[PDB]
Length: 167
Ligand SMILES: Cc1ccc([C@H](CC(=O)O)NC(=O)c2ncnc3[nH]ccc23)cc1
Image (cartoon, rainbow, N blue to C red; front, side, top):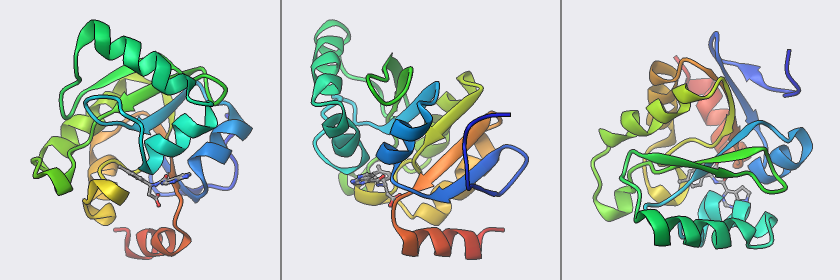
């Protein structure tokens, strides 16, 4: 039993809700919140911009130190950093950005990072400003993640379409 509330159950392990991931994180304080990161951990917009704003830019300060030490992530890769006031940990995961021409096949690799964590709050990777089809992203999520994932879809209209079209 966990603290996530109001999710529709899509599969044995995947749940979905129309919710702002920032507000959901502040309420649940999950062990792991997933960020829709880029390789530079520059959290300027999209999900990352919103999460970072909610940390009063502390996420960005920590991220800049991480990059200065380790260099950029790989597309499809991840790193674990602090969750600040939102969660115990933030798993920064880099899905491919279609508006940068990156191979959508790397989306499965990106979701594989979720399997290292027993429970996660997460957005659909490569969705929104990353330009991928969110319906496809949901399919890859369900077919790749085996741990318990609670997906927050900010757009109510997109949420209804994701549910109604789910196979
Ligand atoms: C790569 C990538 C980018 C964004 C997203 C989802 C799309 C969605 O689920 O609608 N965006 C958000 O979560 C979002 N975007 C902007 N400001 C926000 N403030 C609180 C939440 C929030 C998914 C995947």
